[PDB]
Amino acid sequence: KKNSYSYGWSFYFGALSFIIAEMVGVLAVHMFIDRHKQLTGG
């Protein structure tokens, strides 16, 4: 006990990649719904 292990570096890059990929996905759904609403009207 009392080892004080650190999660250090690029494990955080995996975490940031999660956040970035999810923001990408939600913007993709934005593009779908707006692009379909464009061919709705007249």
Image (cartoon, rainbow, N blue to C red):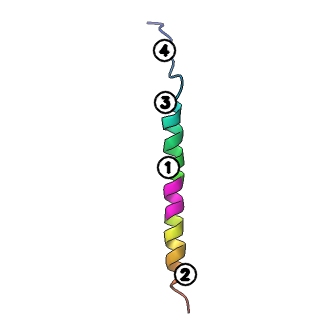
Mark-to-mark CA distance, 2 and 1: 26 Å
Task: Identify residue type, mark 1.
Answer: Ala
Please report whichever mark, 1 or 4, sits nearer to the chain's N-terminal start: 4
Task: Identify residue type, mark 2.
Answer: Gln
Please identify the quarter of the rendering in which residue 1 is found: top left
Horizontal and vertical percent for residue 31? Answer: 53, 68
Mark-to-mark CA distance, 3 and 1: 15 Å
Q: Residue most toward the left?
A: 1
* As drawn, 13 above or below 27: above
Horizontal and vertical percent for residue 42? Answer: 56, 93
Secondary structure character of the magenta stretch overall: helix
Mark-to-mark CA distance, 2 and 3: 41 Å
Specify the label residue 38 is tagged with. 2
- How many marks can you see? 4
* As drawn, 39 above or below 18: below
Horizontal and vertical percent for residue 3? Answer: 47, 8
Residue range in magenta is 24-28
Mark-to-mark CA distance, 1 and 4: 28 Å
Please report whichever mark, 3 or 1, sits nearer to the chain's N-terminal start: 3
Mark-to-mark CA distance, 2 and 4: 53 Å
Please report whichever mark, 2 or 1, sits nearer to the chain's N-terminal start: 1
Q: Which residue is mark 4?
A: 5
Q: Residue at x 50, y 62 (%)?
A: 28
Label 4 crowd bin: few (<14), some (14–19), many (20+), radius 10 Å: few
Q: Secondary structure at mark 2?
A: helix
Horizontal and vertical percent for residue 16? Answer: 54, 39
Label 3 crowd bin: few (<14), some (14–19), many (20+), radius 10 Å: few
Task: Identify residue type, mark 4.
Answer: Tyr
Q: Which residue is mark 3?
A: 11
Q: Which residue is mark 1?
A: 21
Q: Residue at x 50, y 37 (%)?
A: 15
